[PDB]
Image (cartoon, rainbow, N blue to C red; front, side, top):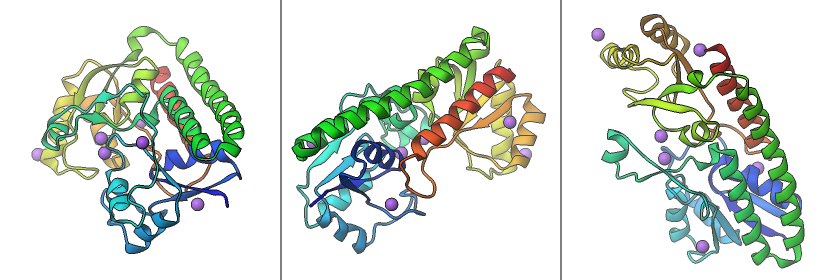
Length: 275
Ligand code: NA
Ligand code: NA
Ligand code: NA
Ligand code: NA
Ligand code: NA
Ligand code: NA
């Protein structure tokens, strides 16, 4: 009776939940506790696609697993929502991105303005599939966007207090590229991620060497290093390492996206205010 909407990544559960409310069912494609980098979808997950009416996709490199799961299902021609259709995309850069054939950065969801565009795109397409609830989906998308804009405005107001020189930062990877660009942060250099969260002494040395060579004091890292590594990096290079949430862990909830974006924007503001 109610429309059954498939979702891939955690932010899309928040988007769809806030758009539909109780009027439709929001169905995660892959279970909570599992990251699709790497996790192999079960027959149970593929069978579930046969119970859905539409699948919302990031569709720009964030959820390639979803298109493969759909092709193997009982509904390969199921309606799909390309959430990023109207979102201007950022290039994926570095040795790793080039070596993987990655053209675009898919983390559009870490931008508030991009999330608003995706929410409006989902709400429009959902109403085409379920005309009876089209008015409600639009009204909910408007209320959701309003809350999201207030979050963007609040962070932008707190950064307005800070001088333009403080906005010169650097990164380890490009995971937060859409967020940093949106909040007017100038990325001086991008240090290529080497060796994971627990790098070898040789891999850590190379990172510290690349960091001390920089003229910035704040670094946003894609790699969430344990405190001992952070402590060593900071003491040996004089930079301050900050990590943000990629909104990809634990339970699916309607509030997850906004709760974690609030915190990410708190870290960015704290980083610049402390510099
Ligand atoms: Na990716
Ligand atoms: Na489509
Ligand atoms: Na990345
Ligand atoms: Na060494
Ligand atoms: Na720190
Ligand atoms: Na759930």
